[PDB]
Length: 106
Length: 106
Image (cartoon, rainbow over all chains, first blue to last red; front, side, top):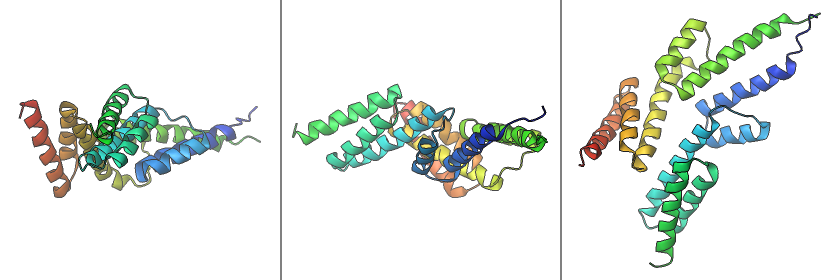
């Protein structure tokens, strides 16, 4: 040609580097906000969502353990909505039901 | 005319993408080895080893809280060996012992 016409490719790649940098150097929320708004497909995203969902379950569990069932419920539902990972689903669903039991006075 | 420097940039960015992927999803040693081999200049390189140790502690702790003690053991031992920080090693050691108690049936 000898034009390579790489600009579109490189600007996508720049954004995916920026996404990885947000994951490494910033909060999960900053990372996912950027990925969502730039519409990026990040390889291994599911693993990252699973890890964050697991962190949310842990937060809920600590709230559950202080009998803040209402607040705990919020975290389990968040975890459920964040990751479609099968273990996350089962564990979050378990704890969600435990909250519901306590909330019903059972 | 064409801009071959953008193609060079492409090669650099592909490598940098792979580096970040190794950092996030693989062991620090693999990331280190790849960066050295490719002579990449990663921004914040000197920060990453301790950051990795910390993320391993966090991920290990969330596995611990979801009662995956066998899985968590791996994260804690890796963090124990990767960190150069005595406080971080105390955290890792504490959880490692708890995981071992779980493997033993307490």
